[PDB]
Length: 261
Length: 25
Length: 76
Image (tube, rainbow over the protein chains, first blue to last red):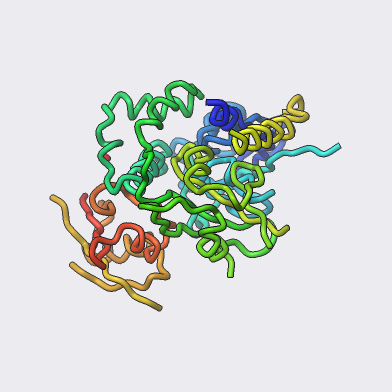
């Protein structure tokens, strides 16, 4: 379990900047800026509690009943979806310092296609990702619907408590040595250029394609490039099945990010 | 066997490059 | 615009939608017919797709005989 262990350890430096609208005129500097170590395999929203705890004593409003506003993360004045692994959002945007800069924002109009944060069950969404992944792999979602309620719960809990053993045990109960399809998502940079993303249908029954073999579906996302998966370069002669079974994210999907060579 | 070694090595670098200056965070 | 067949299967009716649209739009399309909000959609009654997923793509992936079966109700 060497590779996966390395993926579970993936961690980024995150600079969280709290908009002034959240705080009271005069509050100190330290409250407005959080510095944290966030895993690649998790959701930003899983660290919101940590942000509330640090800025609650300076809120410029009563969060219990004052009014209804929406909260969401932003990168360079651009809404960021929290429903993607942190590592995936990173690859998507990327002495030399490597860090992710996030800005907390509030508003009345919730940005289009953005799911609100603090009406947002991260655990439910996540569980469904794995449901979908199970169906794509087996043609049915029975393997995950067979987990006891406890396992499903121990499963999400491993992400929060960061328990590798539990995650590996449950996530394993959802895999195939002979998948019908590959749960694959392809994206481009949100930073430079235009942004596109796709979920091509890639049958596996009786085949063993390499990225090259399916470059047709890969290059389609944006109509020589480099294939980035889990923050690293991937050889085009690599087997799709091995790449999936080894580098898939904590939500069950394999993500490929294309970057200009 | 060998592709795994390349995977294991690139990720190991990744973690280290991404952990650099983690003292500031 | 290639349009494909969606099958709205109540749990507890066949319409053509453009492949270019998102699942969120399909949900909204349904809510506008039922005039509700307490409506959850699931492909083949197994999982709820992310609202941002492309219907055309969901279709190519999970279509049952040309029809993309979308179940709906008011855990899984």
